[PDB]
Image 1 (spheres, rainbow, N blue to C red):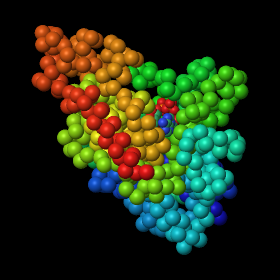
Image 2: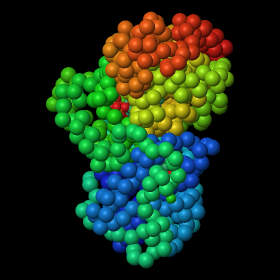
Image 3: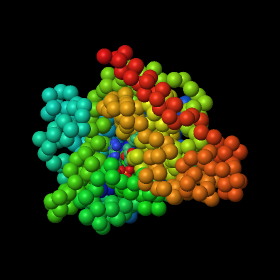
Length: 491
Ligand SMILES: Cc1cc2nc3c(=O)[nH]c(=O)nc-3n(C[C@H](O)[C@H](O)[C@H](O)COP(=O)(O)OP(=O)(O)OC[C@H]3O[C@@H](n4cnc5c(N)ncnc54)[C@H](O)[C@@H]3O)c2cc1C
Ligand SMILES: O=c1nc2n(C[C@@H](O)[C@H](O)[C@@H](O)CO)c3cc(O)ccc3cc-2c(=O)[nH]1
Ligand SMILES: [Cl-]
């Protein structure tokens, strides 16, 4: 008799889930499992806000509903996978364990340990690729055994390899449930908890809801305008747009696997077929999925990718240990409203537009404050709802000119950058209410408002909103000087 586990970690969906499909095939009982793992709650190492963790819980609640609707049940097991799984293998008479492959450092250690244990229990292990467009090992293999290090040569590689696989079909309308009266499957030990019960003190404030149903809705909303999809150009999109964000906001759903990257890609290709002037990579929407694939592919084959030291793709730079600069940045009190509004969005929504992530990451690292990208990445690791190990590392290295990108003379202005999109400062008025009534003339530079104007707007620099912590002209020149010297020490 076939008794199977479908183990969810990412891949939090029923659509495009070949793992799930294999688990159901010829099965008497299927046990859908997510292991609520203490590794992600020990705030010592690994950081997570209530925003992200509650987005996860919402996604698990949506899975529960999808499984309940098909005659089954999601089991949220508490514990370390190494010690939970041997128990349930025996208790449930498990013959097959299915899960979606992942390539992160923790995933590799965890997944090796669970395979060894599975083999000891006589349990078959089935691990299809479906978090990424392609099997990332296959790509490296086809490229002659190393990952390409530019987006251009990565794009050429995948064009030679061909289209990603189709989304797998939808799973059956009825699924075999867990067997009755299994003690590790007791409802009360296996329900989706709340953020309160997991132990978060403060409520989540983000406006984006977790789960596959929300992911599919947001995918559908995006594809209701095929000209927009066809003509999408990432660098030409507006980072100050918040009522209707200028990009898809599909990142947290792709991060958790509430949305299938292959579904998204197949949908793009349908549109591109009927729209022959469609944008091409890297700026196109397909280009965006390829950035993701690119950084996963490089990231999974490089040791210490998420660090500077011991990381072969990363420049060793003499970053300042400057806790007050980092704290001002982290706590949204740099005195540059563009920067502080974005850092407020980070902590409220857990999502900003890519170019707002550029402004704040450039400002922290190579642009003004010369703090290590690792400090920035950690702050993003806590607050981003789309926090992705490889994508966050790679973009921080890109923005600090530590890897992939070397043009350290290009520095974004914390005053001018947003102003060319949003001269009235609508974005700033949203995320920093204290500047609601400041005239647009002064909103990017409130320290240049006459004192009469500051008082009239109820926002006096130094009292209600802080003075700027640097002079951008002085800070950037110094930072460019230090970057030049670090590059010359490297050669
Ligand atoms: C300092 C810094 C840190 C970042 N950290 C993260 C992170 O932790 N997680 C994360 O998903 N993205 C990260 N990004 C990339 C990018 O900013 C987000 O993926 C994007 O803003 C998400 O919005 P969207 O879903 O509307 O993307 P769209 O423009 O709609 O693109 C669709 C999808 O493509 C992928 N994608 C888009 N841009 C990029 C990119 N530059 N690199 C890799 N993949 C991309 C994402 O999965 C995204 O959902 C970071 C960028 C910077 C500059
Ligand atoms: O299997 C789990 N995956 C969790 N993941 C999912 C993955 O990151 C996955 O476990 C691994 O593939 C990462 O190495 C989380 C992701 C977040 O962004 C935030 C919190 C979690 C928590 C968990 C968890 O408790 N259990
Ligand atoms: Cl709990």
